[PDB]
Structures are given as structure tokens and as C-alpha cells.
Amino acid sequence: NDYLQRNAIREDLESYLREMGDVTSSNIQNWLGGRLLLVEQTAQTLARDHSPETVSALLEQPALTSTFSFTYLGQQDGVFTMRPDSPMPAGYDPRSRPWYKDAVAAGGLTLTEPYVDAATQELIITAATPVKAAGNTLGVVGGDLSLKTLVQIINSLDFSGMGYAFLVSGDGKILVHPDKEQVMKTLSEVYPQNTPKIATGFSEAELHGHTRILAFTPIKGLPSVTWYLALSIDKDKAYAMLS
Ligand code: MET
């Protein structure tokens, strides 16, 4: 019976994809979490000493400079200190920036979606948290992460060559993707006819002439964002490999 045999293969494949999605989501959760905690650790150290000499020395520590492209403190009065050095664009105010507002609105450590960096005019992600001292908010510490770095973490596993992983918001906005052309596009723009639904377990759709299976796994431990790890699998390839 071809129907029972088809369902037998599909259930085995979905079981495997569920397993790959869980571990990859765990992996990016732990990776982002360490970056978040490093930013949190930096803020609480600054909360008890934020003199210019100390701010500079702390941001230059190699645990920070080797982890983030840049680490910085934007203060409540608008003053901005960033390491490593970078030329500054005219009219910059850290308080108007997405990372600063997101941290303040979150009331704690959070991650931005990709936004246009003020200096490089390129997309960047930022781990950010307020600096709190006796209820006062003195500012926000941010740590910048390249989207390429996140693509590499979620694609550490090759998924037996069946496909690839990307990140998507609960709103359907593609945040990081191996194809740079799909970054910040929505699932509806990428799949206009039969759009995959995040809530549904496994969706089938057509991309570039081939049927693909999509599966979305929530990423836990990310305060104030609802992001999913998405697997995009070549359907014909997966069914053939699993006989
Ligand atoms: C001064 S630009 C670099 C800091 C941060 N990524 C921003 O765009 O605001």
C-alpha cells in the first residue's frame, strides 16, 4: 500500500526533523544565552563603577572584543563609549537606537531583530541590557553580533545534506538566512501561494522549483523575543534517502 508506506516514511522523517530542530534550537539558545549573560555581566560591573577610565578598560577586555564586533555603553545623558574604536556618524544619539529602546522597553536583557547599523549602514543584531543602580537606569550596554555568525551556529549540523536552517520571528519575518537575499523578507513574500504556518508542525511548500518541508521550533531562554528555528528540507531528497 503506497499510502501506508508514504506515511511510514513521513513519520520517520518528521521524527528525525523534530530531533534536529530541538537540538539546533537548544544550540542557538545556549549560544545566544552566553552572549546575553556576558552583556548582563558587563552592565552590572558598570553599575558599580562607570568612570570613563573604567568604562574604557572594561570594554577593551578581550573576552568582550573577541566575542562581539563592538561592545558599548550609551548613557542616559547621551554619552557613548564603544570598543574597538570606530569613526562616528554625525548626529548619533544612542538613546534613539533600536538596541537602547528595546532594552529600556524590555526592562532587562534582550536581543534586537536585525537593524541598520548607524556607522556601517549594514544589518546587525545586538544583545542589550539596561544598567541599573538603585532603581535608576544609567544607560544601556550593547553587544553587536553579525548575522553571518548566527547562520553558522544554526547550520553547524548538515542535516544529512537534506537542507538548511534559518531564523524567523513569530510574525513571520526571516531574521538570518544562508541566502542573504531572503534576510528580512517574510514567509509570505518567499512563499506567496501556500505560505508555511509557524504554528503547524510540518508544512510543504515550493521554493525555486523544488518541494520543501518546513518545520519550526521555538527557541527558549530569549527574553522579550519570540523567535523560531526553521528547518527547510528538500522533500524529494529526504524521501529518497530514507527509502
Ligand atoms: C555607533 S554605530 C554602532 C553601534 C550600534 N550597532 C548602532 O547602530 O547604534
Image: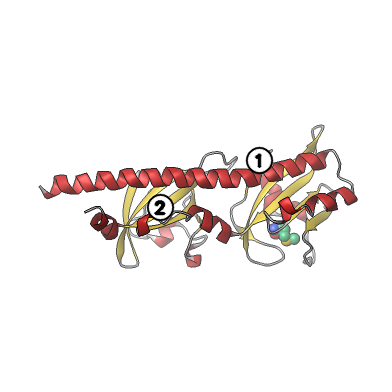
| Circle 2 crowding by C-alpha within 10 Å: few under 14, some 14–19, many from 20 | many
**Which quadrant is home to the C terminus?**
bottom left
Q: Name the residue under label 1.
A: 106
Instruction: Specify the farthest residue to the left.
Output: 1
Going by the numbered disc 1, the residue's amino acid type is Ala
Which of labels 1 and 2 is toward the front? 2
Q: Residue at x 81, y 55 (%)?
A: 80
Instruction: Decide which of tag 1 and tag 2 comes sooner along the chain.
Output: 1
Element marked by disc 2? strand
Query: In which of the image's four quarters is ligand 1 placed?
Result: bottom right
Q: Can residue 58 be seen in this view?
A: yes
- Horizontal side of 128 relative to 188 (left or right) equals right
**Vertically, is 101 above or below 152?**
above
Q: Name the residue under label 2.
A: 231
The answer to the question of whether label 1 and label 2 lie on touching residues, with beta carbons closer than 8 A, is no
State the residue in front, 137 or 56. 56
Residue 51: give x, y in percent of width and height: 89, 47
Please give the label number shown on residue 93. Answer: none
- Horizontal side of 203 relative to 120 (left or right) equals left
